[PDB]
Amino acid sequence: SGSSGYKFGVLAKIVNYMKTRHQRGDTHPLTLDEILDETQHLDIGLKQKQWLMTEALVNNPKIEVIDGKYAFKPKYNVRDKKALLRLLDQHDQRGLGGILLEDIEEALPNSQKAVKALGDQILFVNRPDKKKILFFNDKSCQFSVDEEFQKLWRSVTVDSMDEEKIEEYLKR
Amino acid sequence: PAALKRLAKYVIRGFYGIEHALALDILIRNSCVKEEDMLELLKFDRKQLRSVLNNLKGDKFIKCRMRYFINYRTLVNVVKYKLDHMRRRIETDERDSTNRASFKCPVCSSTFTDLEANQLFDPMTGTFRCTFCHTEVEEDESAMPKKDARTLLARFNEQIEPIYALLRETEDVNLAYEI
């Protein structure tokens, strides 16, 4: 199971506590010795301590370092906002899984960008709505097929067999 | 199946909505498509992805490439069948039907034949009067879609053929190239 140090949940726990105590009122930058210290989990083992400091707080995609201390700051980088034509023309992963984990807020609420995004190639699909927001773009519905619902509704046989032959017999 | 993939491009643009179409786009590459990979890549809901997959399974698409890990396939042999049954239903209605021409008095909701109100037909008013009450009848008891549906059903899939011509030709080429 890859690499494990001491007790599982130290990361998903250190970040959460740090978040929690900061929300609670203790609002100042910390250190890895400092969370350990304040929870007296200091005896996590130097190896784990080190692995947590160098890697756990490096593999975190949203952790904020000015230098010594680690902060929240979900916005860790400057979002590219618009002009994602590179991701739109990246036709190697079907749009590369567009998600709202950094979209919205920035310098703009998605909608304003989207309308232009709607105006442009950019395509927005809130099928899961608030839970999942995604962007993929190209070949919009070519035709509608009047009564496509009815043609799909008429054919609801599924498993039944002996139908392919009845096709040719009706065309003969 | 190069001209079949080109057809796949035309059917997913003429039939399905985007939720289906995005999944169908992945089906483009018939090399290897894991359930875990397709879930993570699409970021669709697992229950919902299972619904779409189950729907595609209903189309006969996937050939359960079980390891368990599954690779998805495409088996739409009903394409040349749906058309036969759709065209049947189009022609059935477009053709003709008997017209129930009869009179009906809106006040007493009594029912009359064209014959019933003919004896009633009142020559002083040039129209048809109900029996026990002189309130005027209804012009037609029932109307059967026939010649108006005739026009829009002669412009049904026949008018969605030109935008289907791209795929009609490319599939005829699949059906012909692969012999």
Image (tube, rainbow, N blue to C red):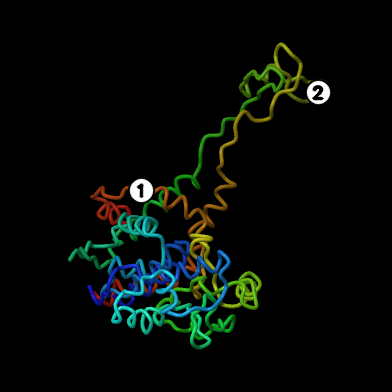
Check residue A10 in the rendering and tell me which mark sits there, or answer none.
none
For the residue marked with disc 2, what is the amino acid? Thr
State the quadrant of the C terminus of chain A: bottom left
In this rendering, position of residue A128 left or right of residue B130: left
> In terms of secondary structure, where does tag 2 sit?
loop
Tag 2 residue: B125
Image quadrant of residue B128? top right
Q: Is B165 drawn above or below residue A31 in the view shown?
A: above
Q: Nearer the viewer, residue B57 or A26?
A: A26
Disc 2 crowd, CA 10 A, few/some/many (<14, 14-19, 20+): few
Q: Is residue A28 above or below residue B104?
A: below
- Give the labeled residue for mark 1: A156
Residue in front for this viewpoint, A156 or A86: A86
Instruction: Say which of B28 and A75 sits in front.
Output: A75
Disc 1 + disc 2, Cβ < 8 Å: no
Image location of residue B25, percent across then percent down: 39, 71
Residue A64 percent across, percent down from the top left:
51, 81
C-alpha gap between disc 1 and disc 2: 54 Å
Q: Position of residue A149 (x, y in %)?
A: 47, 52
Please tell me in which quadrant of the rendered image residue B173 appears: bottom left
Which image quarter holds the N terminus of chain A? bottom left
Query: SS at mark 1?
Result: loop
